[PDB]
Image (cartoon, coloured by chain):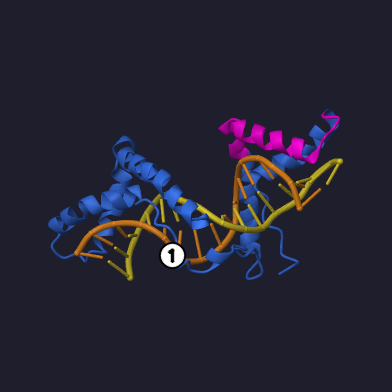
Chain colours: A blue, B yellow, C orange
Amino acid sequence: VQDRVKRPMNAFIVWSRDQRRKMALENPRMRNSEISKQLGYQWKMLTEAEKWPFFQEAQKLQAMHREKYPNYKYRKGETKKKFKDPNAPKRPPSAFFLFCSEYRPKIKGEHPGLSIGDVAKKLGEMWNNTAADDKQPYEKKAAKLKEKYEKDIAAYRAK
DNA sequence: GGGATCTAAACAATGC
DNA sequence: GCATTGTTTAGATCCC
């Protein structure tokens, strides 16, 4: 495990590698902290047009990497929540699931021969049909709850 | 359980 | 190792 196979470098690292070297040239003091600090800054300040193809480098990396190694590979070096976390804070209900809940009684209405779990399948195809603007309110609702959820996970980190 | 998208802790590497 | 932020991973999310 110590000689763990290197995980596919995320797009940030790709950029960081060549950028850091250039930065060392341009910046006279080139302090590790200072170089990297603004380095990450510029990255997130970059345009998505730049991110996309950089992300593709990482995507191709992980694609070949994951298939290459059958068993030996990056395991989630997590921590307490490495296994099934008994008391993980409850995330905001997913927009899809919110829509599913709303249509659940309706689906059985369409066909009086569906198990409650099977009604989700109906939602699945309607999910694609659902207009982005129409589904947006649900997602926003979850996003608002997400802020609340972060407080919950913060409590998890420290009471 | 059930489809079908989602989340957060932790790690991923360069050049000093 | 640092700091930056991105991919990792594997449960997690609805009602009945």
Q: Residue at x 37, y 45 (%)?
A: A145
Q: Residue at x 67, y 54 (%)?
A: A8
Range covered by the magenta-colored residues: A27-53
Where's residue A59, x and y in %?
60, 49
Name the amino acid, label 1. Asn
Task: Read off the residue under disc 1.
Answer: A87
Tell whether A148 sits left or right of A3.
left
Say whether residue A44 is magenta.
yes
Q: Quadrant of the N terminus of chain A?
A: bottom right
Chain under label 1?
Answer: A
Q: Residue at x 68, y 50 (%)?
A: A9
Tell whether C2 sits left or right of A81.
right
Tell whether B15 sits left or right of A11.
right
Where's residue A101, x and y in %?
24, 53
Instruction: Give above or below for A81 relative to A53.
Output: below
Secondary structure mostly taken by the magenta-highlighted segment of the chain: helix
Q: How many marks?
A: 1
| Label 1 crowd (10 A; few <14 / some 14-19 / many >=20) | few
Q: Which residue is farthest front?
A: A159
Instruction: Give above or below for A42 relative to A114.
Output: above
Is any atom of residue A131 visible in this view? no
Where's residue B3, x and y in %?
34, 60
Is any atom of residue A76 visible in this view? yes
Tell whether C2 sits left or right of A55.
right
Instruction: Give above or below for A159 relative to A44.
Output: below
Say whether residue A47 is magenta.
yes
Instruction: Give above or below for A42 relative to A111.
Output: above
Of the pair B7 and A74, the residue shown nearer to us: B7
Q: Residue at x 33, y 42 (%)?
A: A141
Does dot 1 land on a helix, a strand or a loop? loop
